[PDB]
Amino acid sequence: AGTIAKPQGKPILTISGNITNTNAEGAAQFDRDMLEALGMETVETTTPWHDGRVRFDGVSLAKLMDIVGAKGTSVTAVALNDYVSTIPIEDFKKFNVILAIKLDGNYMTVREKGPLFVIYPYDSDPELQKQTYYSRSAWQVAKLIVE
Ligand SMILES: [Cl-]
Ligand code: NA
Ligand code: NA
Ligand code: NA
């Protein structure tokens, strides 16, 4: 039986891998309404890719790992362009990493590297202002695979 509700709209995120809570064969599929329903956090920061300080609204990745019952310690983020970013799951609770859904109050289209973007609060901690965390940021996210 499924433990995650089925999406009513077009799924924009699939979580798979070593998870226990699903709504499809070995996977948890989310439409945008389901992601927004998990609760939206706000992160304001300068970044290597944006002009000036920008504001992201998105869902806590720690909350996504909790609802799918992630059993791993690493997540592979798969982008639309088929390149991956590898992220230690420990980063999610340590730095309040979000799966961004909005940028400056607007949804993100494909040419803005949306609809989903893994974002760290770079300016909140000097530790996050370096390539280690810029490479763990993942734009055009389509999938999260728990290893
Ligand atoms: Cl577009
Ligand atoms: Na699975
Ligand atoms: Na936009
Ligand atoms: Na990346």
Image: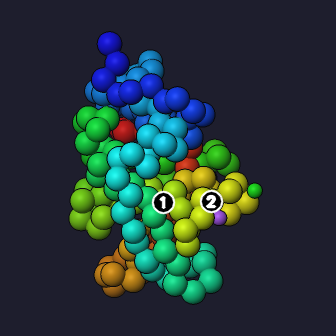
Q: Residue at x 49, y 30 (%)?
A: 7
Q: What amino acid type is highlighted by mark number 2?
A: Met
Percent of width and height locating residue 40: 38, 58
Upstream in sequence: badge 2 or badge 1: 1
Q: Which residue is mark 2?
A: 108
Q: Split into 4 quadrants, where in the image is the C terminus?
A: top left
Q: Tags 2 and 1 in contact by the CB under 8 Å rule?
A: yes
Name the residue that disc number 1 marks.
Answer: 100
Pick the residue in front: 75 or 119: 119
Rendered residue at 24%/65% (across/down)? 94
Q: Amino acid at mark 1?
A: Ala
Task: Look at the numbered disc 2 and give the secondary structure of its residue.
Answer: loop
Q: Where 44 sits versus 109, above or below?
A: below
Q: Quadrant of residue 20?
A: top left
For the residue labelled by badge 1, is the local secondary structure a helix, a strand or a loop?
strand
Q: Is residue 82 above or below residue 115?
A: above
Residue at mark 2 to residue at mark 1: CA–CA distance: 9 Å
